[PDB]
Length: 209
Length: 50
Length: 49
Image (cartoon, rainbow over all chains, first blue to last red; front, side):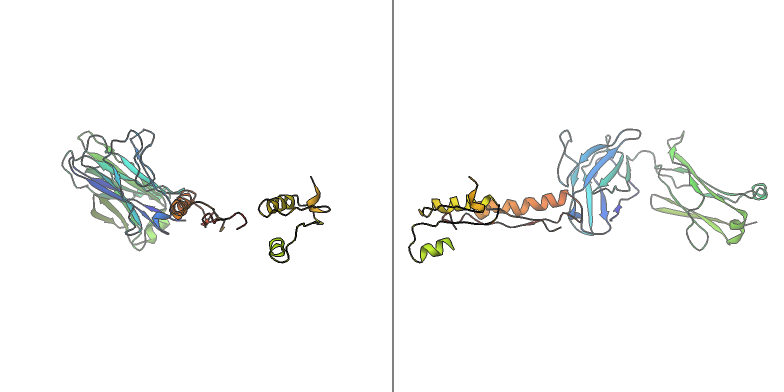
């Protein structure tokens, strides 16, 4: 089977175009047809572009489609406008969906996220539990990629990250929680909470005691 | 066979026969008759069913 | 697998869409079980031919 690649998110100002590419892992893209879809928050997905270069009835043009081979990828091109098209787009070829790219208008000025790593409390360690608390805030847009590595390899066991959501100051907030045991807490030298936001990576590391 | 025989000595009749049950042989022979003007009388075998 | 489908269609220009259309069907139906092929031939003169 193949696998579909989409960028996590992208930001574009009104009056300018934006391109998002759907990439096929194995095999050629032209071997099968591809489709593009949009989904508003809480709204059912709606067809926007189907069968490579074909506009469904009701689609007001603008949204074109590139199916050139290139690096085994097919991209989606949108005319310059930011009225409502700020949504998440997915590519589907054959029983496989795309990752999805978040698109939003350029509103408030972008703010760098604030990374803070909280080592597990001693009282929790007494209860044979270890929770790693990582908090993020003052960032735009609400899309943060957070990864956890035990100083020698990424760790995905017990990780728990809150979905970003709009704050009360036209901003976004989120947090990441990692659940571990005292044996795992004391087994590794340090644990890292990497934060990725709009291509910006901020690293904060903590050590036991 | 049929039209090479026709191309050989000039026959006028091709009294025929068979041993199978494939009804399709009747239609093929009927097609032979149209474009060659040779009377043919199938008797026994596949070329028997009306 | 290789399920070849033929035709006795008219002049080769009309046959061109046949070779084009099958790939479209191949593109639509996605599996490694349905790899069709194509062949054709024009209307030769005479009936026996």
